Image (cartoon, rainbow, N blue to C red; front, side, top):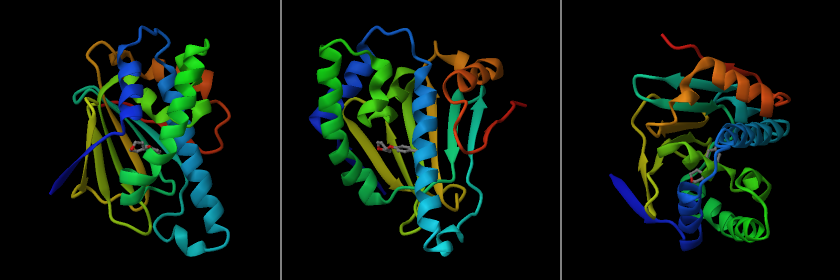
Length: 209
Ligand SMILES: OCc1ccc(OC2CCOCC2)cc1
């Protein structure tokens, strides 16, 4: 069972701007996604100090980067707090409406796309390099869900029947045909060292077979 939702008009406008604006410094997408993962890990860590059973779904707090040249995907996996169905459909979009408006106004005043994370909508930088993004997520209080969007104004949510994740989020970037540099080990290493060197969780870059 697949449910299809319309983005709020403001978020659809943001995604079109990201897809259509000429902007060569695309590599910042990875910093933004790693930052989101780090924030999600911070959140479950803090909650676990007062309810240690919140880690029954997995004690390890980490970020994995998994390139796959056969599928042309880059996957960013974290074992953070995860998101509920309500997060995916309602809560995050509500927060993203105000962040988008601030970001859009900042861009009109001379900011550039790399500053997107200062407005809390860094996830959408994924569309600098991906034609489709799939988000698989599992929160302790809800079921495992798959969110997906190729932009165009809509996204889908379904219950996920794949490999159970325990807790956390996987962002699968289905890369654009001309963005396969972000599947190369040396390129990912370079970007992590440049932009994500002090993240407080282990980042493991998987090697391809
Ligand atoms: O833990 C990583 C992560 C992944 C995606 C996120 O944002 C939502 C934005 C649009 O709706 C689908 C998900 C936030 C955090």
